[PDB]
Image (cartoon, rainbow, N blue to C red; front, side):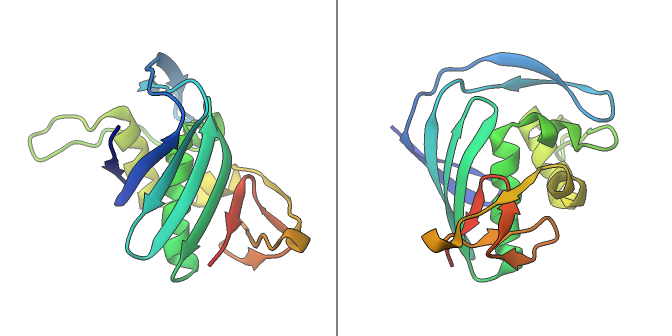
Length: 163
């Protein structure tokens, strides 16, 4: 039906539904945010000049993120955007400080953009609370660790690398 841009990446759905839903979450700084949650399985591609990815997800959970990029750091940039987009609660909980990002008109960025801006600042807490898991490298799936170390043994939950 159509694309969009978020976090410096063009998104493009390739399966799943666009119904809305409101939910209140609580950050790790005890601030309340009101977010628009897509309930159901949806699948997107993500494209930016130094990385591209496939993102599969369901309700407030990332199923799978396969990413390719020029290197570890361009790959990390794809990962942070997908984690924020996932909307998972370990993501919401990784927030420190109040989020009050604004445009040049002193209007609030929307809640999703509040999260994105926070984690673009720095994703260390995000990555450390996300969860790691074993990988099968007999299937060619490369892993990446919370510190950006590539590994053939583990990876941050749901994340795999392919270039």
